[PDB]
Image (spheres, coloured by chain):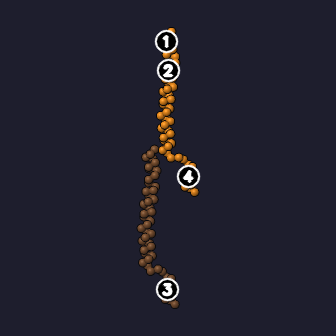
Chain colours: A brown, B orange
């Protein structure tokens, strides 16, 4: 029964590590794209004016 | 809805600037022709006698 109960304890650490790594990689791309999105259009329009 | 609402806020700046430039160009022609029209009548007649 202690073998049976210790089957919902935690995931095999590898997959949780993989999820952490993938999300951490994706966050920085989000941040960079947000920066460029803030930068572009208003500067372009001010150049037009 | 914030994308939908901000479609009746303002036009593009390009056509507004085009309107501004066209009106400014036409106004000076009006002014010069008004000056010539005022100069025309009496000066050409004053030598009637």
The residue carrying mark 1 is B47
Alpha carbon separation for disc pair 4 and 2: 52 Å
Q: Secondary structure at mark 2?
A: helix
Q: Residue furthest top?
A: B49
* Picture coordinates of residue B49, whole percent (x, y): 51, 9
Tell which circle, 4 or 2, labels the residue nearer the N-terminal end: 4
Element assignment for label 3: loop
Camera-nearest residue between A48 and B46: B46
Structural distance between the alpha carbons of marks 3 and 2:
106 Å
Q: CA distance from mark 2 to mark 1?
A: 14 Å
Neighbor class of circle 2 (other Cα within 10 Å; few <14, some 14-19, many 20+) is few
Residue at x-position 46% and y-position 55%: A38
Q: Identify the subunit bearing mark 3.
A: A
> Percent position (x, y) of residue B44?
49, 16
Residue drawn at x 48%, y 41% is B17
Label placed on residue A6: 3
Pair 3/1: label in front: 1
Q: CA distance from mark 3 to mark 4?
A: 56 Å
Answer yes or no: are tags 3 and 4 on the same subunit: no
CB contact under 8 Å: marks 3 and 2: no
Numbered disc 1: secondary structure = loop
For the point 50% across and 32% down, which residue is it?
A: B27
Q: Please provide percent x and percent y for residue A47.
A: 43, 46
User: Which picture quadrant has residue A13?
Assistant: bottom left
Q: Are marks 3 and 4 in contact (CB under 8 Å)?
A: no
Please, which chain is the residue tagged with disc 1 on?
B
Rendered position, B13 above or below B5: above
Residue pointed to by mark 2: B39
Q: Which residue is mark 4?
A: B6
């Amino acid at each position: 029964l202690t073998a049976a109960e210790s089957r919902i304890r935690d995931l095999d650490i590898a997959d949780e590590m993989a999820k952490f790594t993938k999300n951490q990689i994706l966050a920085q791309s989000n941040i960079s794209m947000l920066a460029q999105a803030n930068s572009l259009p208003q500067m372009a329009l001010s150049l037009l004016g």
